[PDB]
Image 1 (cartoon, rainbow, N blue to C red):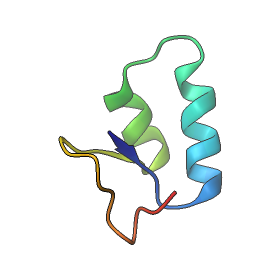
Image 2 (image 1 turned 30 degrees about the horizontal axis):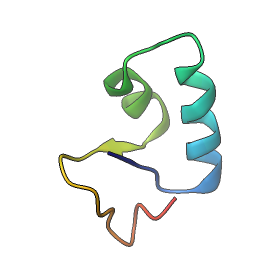
Image 3 (image 1 turned 60 degrees about the horizontal axis):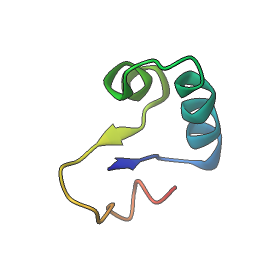
Image 4 (image 1 turned 135 degrees about the vertical axis):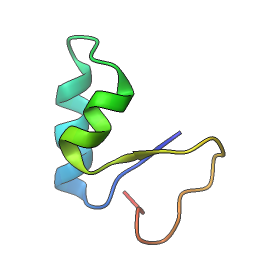
Length: 46
């Protein structure tokens, strides 16, 4: 599951993913994170 730190970061992440870029590269590009569970923490609420 992906968790983003702000709405801007999530919007940038979704654009990064349009061409098919792996989530891990979009994560470091935007500040979003990938976790194995489904419950994002409060500081990555977007």
